[PDB]
Amino acid sequence: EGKITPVSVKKVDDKVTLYKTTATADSDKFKISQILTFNFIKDKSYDKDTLVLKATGNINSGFVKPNPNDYDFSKLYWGAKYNVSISSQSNDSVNVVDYAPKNQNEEFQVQNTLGYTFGGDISISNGLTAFSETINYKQESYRTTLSRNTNYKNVGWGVEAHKIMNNGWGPYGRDSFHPTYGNELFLAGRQSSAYAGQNFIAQHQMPLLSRSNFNPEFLSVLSHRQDGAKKSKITVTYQREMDLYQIRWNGFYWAGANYKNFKTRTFKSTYEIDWENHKVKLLDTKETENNK
Ligand SMILES: C[N+](C)(C)CCOP(=O)(O)O
């Protein structure tokens, strides 16, 4: 649910003209917000039309705190992985050619610059030309990877829990497991004389992405061959994988268990890109849930 701004035009040289329009689609229910800025680059010195899409917005973590009254067993849900996907769903003249980030990255702050040079050259550099854009996001304790299904018409990224320190313990991940204590990701004490509901570390000691939200900044470059249809379809998906983290007292010690992607919340928008008129039109939005 949202709006699409009118198109703004910026004539660079006599060769290049930039056109921009921003679309916003939201899921109030899942607390996901997609802000999509389509930058069309018309370059007379290049035999292809270029589109630089910047995807920003918000994806809530889906965090659910534990019931403090839980005595011997308790659980909480946390935002373990954020997935953003872009797909060219029609028109064989259109392909996904470049993107940022373009490689795995576990730095606390991801910063990249994408530049377009007169003549068609796309360059991506680390840190913050006829056109330029940047991506900047914080992902402390998490790691960004390029989705396995990335190909000539598809690009995706995953921002997943990676190296999470408890106090000085760790690092722990979605898969860590101690032969005795299980996954200790958010376990406060192995022998705590406490209610289970009160034996997790505090929210402020957990990564911001795990208990708050993720503010994505991703860039995808689509190329149009200048032959065939002027319009094409594109889908943009924002998703969170929520893990069920639970702790239990067995009479002797505390042990933890993390169920990976136990709950999934997904928001997908479908737009029709009009490469001739530098506009986009919302065709559909779809909210989908998975609950194991
Ligand atoms: C914090 N931890 C539960 C992951 C490791 C053990 O801590 P502790 O029970 O020795 O205080």
Image (tube, rainbow, N blue to C red):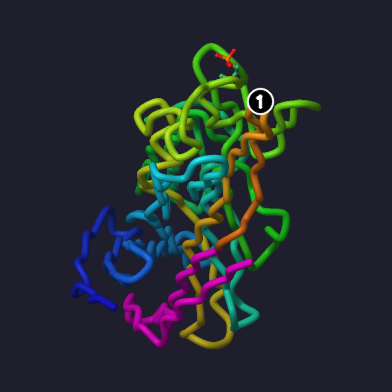
**Location of ligand 1 given as a quarter of the image:** top right
Q: Residue at x 22, y 59 (%)?
A: 10
Residue at 52% across, 22% down: 192
Give the amino acid type for the residue marked by disc 1 in the picture: Tyr
Q: What are the residue bounds of the magenta stretch?
A: 264-292
Q: Nearer the viewer, residue 31 or 236?
A: 31
- Please provide percent x and percent y for residue 241: 56, 55
Residue 290 falls inside the magenta stretch:
yes
Residue at 35% across, 48% down: 131
- The vertical placement of 224 against 228, above or below, is above
Identify the residue position indicated by label 1 in the image: 253
Instruction: State the predominant SS element of the stretch in magenta.
Output: strand
Q: Where residue 204 sits: x, y (%)?
A: 35, 29
Q: Quadrant of residue 29?
A: bottom left
List the single residue furthest toward the top.
Answer: 168
The C terminus appears in which quarter of the rendering? bottom right
Percent position (x, y) of residue 26?
Answer: 31, 70
Quadrant in which the N terminus appears: bottom left
User: Residue 36's image quarter?
Assistant: bottom left
Q: Is 282 on the left or on the right of 183, as rendered?
A: left
Q: Residue extending furthest front? A: 251
